[PDB]
Image (spheres, rainbow, N blue to C red):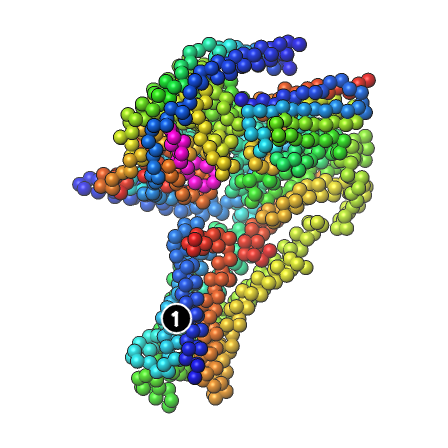
Amino acid sequence: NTASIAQARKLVEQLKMEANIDRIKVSKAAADLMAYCEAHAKEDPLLTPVPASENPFR
Amino acid sequence: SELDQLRQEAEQLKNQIRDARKACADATLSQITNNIDPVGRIQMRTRRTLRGHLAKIYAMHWGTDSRLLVSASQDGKLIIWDSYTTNKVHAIPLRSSWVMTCAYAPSGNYVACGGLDNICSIYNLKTREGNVRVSRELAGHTGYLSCCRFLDDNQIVTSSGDTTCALWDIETGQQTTTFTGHTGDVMSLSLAPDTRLFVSGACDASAKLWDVREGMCRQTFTGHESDINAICFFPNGNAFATGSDDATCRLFDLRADQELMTYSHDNIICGITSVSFSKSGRLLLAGYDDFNCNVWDALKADRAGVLAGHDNRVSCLGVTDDGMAVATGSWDSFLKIWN
Amino acid sequence: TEDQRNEEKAQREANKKIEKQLQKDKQVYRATHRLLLLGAGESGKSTIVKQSGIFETKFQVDKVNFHMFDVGGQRDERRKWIQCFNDVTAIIFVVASSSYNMTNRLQEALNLFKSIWNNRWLRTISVILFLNKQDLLAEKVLAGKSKIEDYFPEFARYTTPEDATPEPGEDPRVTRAKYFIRDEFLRISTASGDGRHYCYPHFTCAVDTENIRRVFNDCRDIIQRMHLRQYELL
Amino acid sequence: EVWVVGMGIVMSLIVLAIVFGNVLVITAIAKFERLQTVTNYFITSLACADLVMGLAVVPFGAAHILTKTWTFGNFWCEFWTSIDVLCVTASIETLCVIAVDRYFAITSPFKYQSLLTKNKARVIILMVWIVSGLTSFLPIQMHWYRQEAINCYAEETCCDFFTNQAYAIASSIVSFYVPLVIMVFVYSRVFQEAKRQLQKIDKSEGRCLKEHKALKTLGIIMGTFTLCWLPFFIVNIVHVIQDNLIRKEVYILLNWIGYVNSGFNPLIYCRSPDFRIAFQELLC
Amino acid sequence: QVQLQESGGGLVQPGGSLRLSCAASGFTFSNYKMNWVRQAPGKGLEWVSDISQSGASISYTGSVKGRFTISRDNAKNTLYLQMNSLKPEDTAVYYCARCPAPFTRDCFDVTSTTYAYRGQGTQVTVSS
Ligand SMILES: Cc1ccccc1CC(C)(C)NC[C@H](O)c1ccc(O)c2c1OCC(=O)N2
């Protein structure tokens, strides 16, 4: 019990520390995800299936 | 009545964080990703089948050349394969038969393993004298070693069943810093591409984001229902996925501090063992206990295809670091490489 | 071409050596019989392993390799590491007999047993049951301050079965109680009814005869009943 | 008569049953890696043996009874007889091998998994096919097995099988009698152990139907191999002892009765759950 | 997040009755096998009673056969434990813990603290 109140104290310090950050908008974050995907989409071998002439595993 | 006031203030704090997160939710990725074209039924086929093991495969890892791969099995054998020409470059017998993890050095020097023997054994491969010997054995956990990964050839972070994570240094063999603050067994971890920070899954259904240099937890994500088996980053580092035993995959953003999306389907009752993205970051591959490997999309959440195969559960999954192929280990001792 | 061909030949030889040694490993490995020893708490599981780390023990009887593993060095949050052992042929489950009074870790052990028996990966693994601390059980029961019937009321309705094998100098109530615990573990095993795996009870360590002989007979039985049931003769 | 179509349709169903069944078994073991066990290598041998049984042997034998004269030539008739004997011997022997496999499993469990490996399995398969060839082809191609005999031999399209005493006794003893004895002793001792185990289980479960479950499976596995081939192989030893004790139609009839056992084999040996799954996955 | 809140409980005469309730949320309550686990004062924990998915399969520890009635409300995600005719041995902290795995029969929960799928508990005390 007395060993647990120290754990509770530490948890209050943890919640205290992670309470104060910056959070950005979901619309912009997801927009960044969409942008990265639409950028690197051409270099993806799983996405555009591989020609067997240039396929290293054939 | 001290514990009561403390728990009240802690719950209140939690409530404030809950509300602050709920306030940032002005749209969804599901709403805005309407115009993005779908994937289509795009399917993979087995180009190579690597068989060498006597017992079940518990893990694998790709190398940075995308050529070699290490796989460990519960017979105590560690086989280092070659992807193209399906050979066996090395076989290292372990001290303990049971091994739950393996890792590859980014420069190709060392290979790490670990398991219920509580000790992370580093093996050198560059021995001019010949075969492989234990280079440095790292012991600091009171529980089993669930997973671990190389930062570089010098320092290595480990995860364990004694609720903790630890960053080691190979030369001194000691713990540089100790990460505590999880609740249950720490099942898996994943490094960053810039390796400044790393996430970890645990048995309290919550994934934590730590920072490697300072050693502090920046954010705690509570979105799942049960134990989180695997966690994998995204190509730019701003998001990550977690599989769990609630039969759902979830995508979390770090700058949004909350769960963005859940991929699930009602015909699933079993957990997700492993996850990973592709090179571009568009596909989310997940192995399940229904013996398949379901390929989801990261944007539209519809499964594009499926990977048939293994006769028993799929333990591990990995993607080549240039994105050229996928590899799936199972409990039928067989590795299948796909394209 | 010029030297890749040599790489092919080198890697070929390495593959040969590894393949060879691995084949030699398969024989000893598949001939080795893996066992999982576990107990709830104050179980006397350290005596059998007194009869690699301190965890693992490999003992040899009649040129038949046994490879035991003790999990006593881990935490009791069990649900992740116990999946690692699905190839183990038998789980030796050792429980104290007079721990009914104080708590009731006998009920905890029963719970753990049911959990293992119904777990979805361990639906194939037979449990060899060792009922320990027989004399101590007898003492507590004859002393009578510690009553089983408090924590098991249905013991008032359970009498000595027809297949009684009494050893003399013993209270028939003590014998009845002993068989009652044994039956409490058996009924859980018979609840499933598929017959893929079975529970073999035993009585232990009041006489310190080597329990390996029981282990032996029961291991033989497990594998014999695996082939027997698979060939539909059972 | 109506005899032509009456027998033709039945023999067509037999040829189709044997072929379709054994082909299905082979393709299942080829297109599933889970079916690649040591026991399954044995059943693959059995399947091949029964496949060549219903592909050449039984159709040309049917053509022989319906047209009652062969056109294809003398050499090809002895060859045909050879491939017949080869398929039969290989079948029976393989059945005996599988029986010995199960006896080794239940009698010596600890040494079972250790000894019986892949190379050992292949060695036994090749051994079986060698003993079957050495008890069929060499006597026929070397003419060790020989009035009416010389007549039918020298006559081209006389498609009769006349053997001397020395070849018929030893040929039958090698293909059938020894495997029968082995199988009887094997399943007997196995049944004894099974009965014992059921006794122990009954002692530890206080919670005749199981005896029935144990007798039925042995009864059918021995019965299908007995009823089909026993009257034939007994007929050969009666035909050697006392001539004109058996008419020539009975011989052909019994031989066919024996052939059908090859068609029953996939049904009495693919009762696995996994076999069933793998079967319906190919039959949609 | 996941929390299970023990409500009810308090100081009651032996031979009385007390209805324990547990409000759950953050998960699909219909699927998860719930159970009640106790921790005695100054002695280790012992499992008491479980309830399955449908509300059919119900077991008790032998000490509390029949006098305890465990019932689940799937319709609003809430759990209930009806205790009747209390005994002096019952005085302990009653936690409502769920089993961690979906769609199963096994549970590993009586195992001690920093197990997240367990509440803070209420105090039930036997009167003098
Ligand atoms: C040539 C012909 C002409 C007319 C009608 C039928 C046939 C077909 C025949 C009788 C040859 N089938 C033989 C049958 O398969 C057979 C196989 C293995 C054996 O070990 C023997 C055996 O029978 C004889 C023996 O003693 N042993």
Q: Is residue B295 magenta?
A: yes
Res. D23 image quadrant: bottom left
In which chain is the residue bearing label 1?
A: D
Query: Residue at the location (46% across, 56% down)?
Result: D39
Residue B293 within the magenta-colored segment of the rendering = yes
Q: Position of residue E49 (x, y in %)?
A: 68, 31
Segment colored magenta = B287-303
Residue E55: percent from the left, percent from the top? 65, 35
Work out whether residue E97 or residue A1 is closer to the camera in this orientation and state it.
E97
Q: Is residue C82 visible from the viewing direction of this image?
A: yes
**In front of the other: C64 or B6:** B6
Residue B142 pos. (x, y %): 52, 24
**In which quadrant of the rendered image does the N terminus of chain A lie?**
top right
Is B272 on the left or on the right of E10, as rendered?
left
Residue B107 rendering spot, x and y as whole percentages: 31, 26
Residue of label 1: D86
| D156 to B155, vertically: above or below | below
Q: Is residue B129 above or below residue E12?
A: below
Quarter of the image with the C terminus of chain A is top left
Ligand 1 lies under 8 Å from the Cβ of mark 1: no
Q: Secondary structure at mark 1?
A: helix
Quarter of the view holding residue C72: top right
Mark 1 is on which residue type?
A: Leu
Q: Residue at x 50, y 83 (%)?
A: D238
Residue name at image x 64 percent, y 55 percent:
D198
Residue C54, placed above or below residue B168:
below
